[PDB]
Amino acid sequence: ADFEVHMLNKAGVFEPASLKVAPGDTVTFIPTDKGHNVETIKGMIPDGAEAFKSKINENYKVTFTAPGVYGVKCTPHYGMGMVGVVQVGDAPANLEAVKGAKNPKKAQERLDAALAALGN
Ligand SMILES: [Cu+2]
């Protein structure tokens, strides 16, 4: 299945900010507003996943196959808290590593909230 995640100004937000998908699903990240991208956060993707970083203002499609939680950021707006979470499958095995990851404060508060929203 195919999902969209939009980057929007309300520094902006990922909408949805938390997203659960199954292994093999695809997410397209779409910067509706200018100035945004998506990039994985170091230490916040599961084993077997590849890091990725899209170009500013480009639509970027990722097929998610490795299970676990993925923390993602907009590269320039990371410090302001523009971040999201994609969870692949139902019982993520990397939760300890991701909860241990250091982030800017505002990024941490949003990451924590997105994780909570997904039941973790
Ligand atoms: Cu941004």
Image (tube, grey):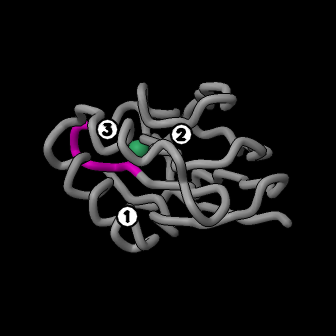
Residue drawn at point x = 51 percent, y = 69 percent = 16
Q: Which residue is mark 2?
A: 38
Of residues 115 and 80, the one drawn nearer to the viewer in this rendering:
115
**Is disc 1 surrounded by few (<14), some (14 to 19) or many (20+) residues within 10 Å?**
many
State the separation of the CA atoms marked 1 and 3: 15 Å
Q: Which residue is mark 3?
A: 78
Of residues 17 and 67, the one drawn nearer to the viewer in this rendering:
67
Q: Is residue 7 magenta?
A: no
- Work out whether 115 lies above or below 83: below
Tell me where residue 89 appears, x and y as whole percent.
Answer: 67, 61
Q: Earlier in the sequence, mark 2 or mark 3?
A: 2
Residue drawn at point x = 65 percent, y = 56 percent = 88
Location of the N terminus by quadrant is bottom right
Label 3 is placed on what type of residue? Tyr
Label 2 is placed on what type of residue? Val
**Is disc 3 surrounded by few (<14), some (14 to 19) or many (20+) residues within 10 Å?**
many
Q: Earlier in the sequence, mark 1 or mark 3?
A: 3
**Is disc 2 surrounded by few (<14), some (14 to 19) or many (20+) residues within 10 Å?**
many
- Work out whether 22 lies above or below 95: below
Asked if disc 2 is less than 8 Å from ligand 1, the answer is: no
Tell me where residue 47 appears, x and y as whole percent.
Answer: 61, 30
Q: Which residue is mark 1?
A: 114
